[PDB]
Image (cartoon, helix red, strand yellow):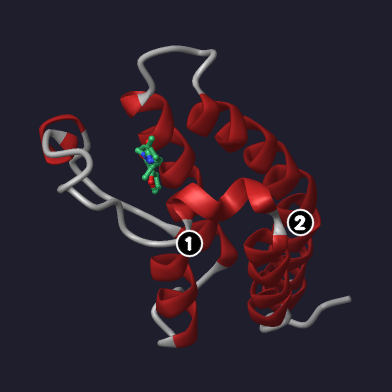
Amino acid sequence: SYDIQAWKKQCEELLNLIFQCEDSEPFRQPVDLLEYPDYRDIIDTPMDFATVRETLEAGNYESPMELCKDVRLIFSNSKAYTPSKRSRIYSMSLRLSAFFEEHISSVLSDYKSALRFHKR
Ligand SMILES: CCCCNC(=O)N1CCN(C(=O)c2ccco2)C[C@@H]1C
């Protein structure tokens, strides 16, 4: 399965599944500072799933590793802001992270395998 470009549609499909998850609601658009006025005091690099989808669709990711780094930033940012491990939004972030990691694993493996085959 040595298609170097196949990761992009696989990531579009995975983002579609993440948007269907009720657990993605809080992460679907850039955080609003009116509700959380100190957000940029704690969070240096805001990230959300709409920004990840737009970056993919603009052709501004070179690899699925770069998309994975941005999705992981959504989850680390949510953790940086949670007042507790028992908070609702943080709890939704942990389930969504587990779902994302379960699905991205093969996308990364296939891509890296395809690049190694190209350079063989
Ligand atoms: C009662 C509050 C309503 C939900 N809002 C809320 O608590 N949020 C702050 C923390 N957060 C994030 O850090 C984050 C990462 C990616 C997108 O947002 C999620 C959400 C916007």
In depth, the one of 20 and 118 nearer the eye is: 20
53 to 105, vertically: above or below? below
Disc 2: which residue: 109
- Name above or below for residue 94 compared with residue 10: above
Where the C terminus falls, by quadrant? Answer: bottom right
Viewer-nearest residue: 74 or 90: 90
Answer yes or no: disc 2 within 8 Å of ligand 1: no
Q: Residue at x 63, y 67 (%)?
A: 15
Q: Residue at x 35, y 54 (%)?
A: 47
Residue 73 image position (x, y, % from top left): 41, 44
The amino acid type, in three-letter code, at marker 1 is Phe
Q: Quadrant of the N terminus?
A: bottom right
65 vs 113, nearest the viewer = 65
**CB contact under 8 Å: marks 2 and 1:** no
Q: Which residue lies at the image location 71% right of the left edge and 54% below the top edge?
A: 104
Percent of width and height locating residue 19: 63, 64
The x, y position of residue 81, in whole percent, is: 32, 27
Q: Secondary structure at mark 1?
A: helix
Of circles 2 and 1, which is in front? Answer: 1
Label 1 CA crowd tier, 10 Å (few <14, some 14–19, many 20+): many
Which callout, 2 or 1, points at the residue further toward the start of the chain?
1
Between the C-alphas of marks 2 and 1, the distance is 22 Å
**Does the beta carbon of the residue at mark 1 sit less than 8 Å from ligand 1?**
yes
Taking the image in four quarters, ligand 1 sits in the one at top left
Kind of element beneath mark 2: helix
Which numbered disc covers residue 49? 1
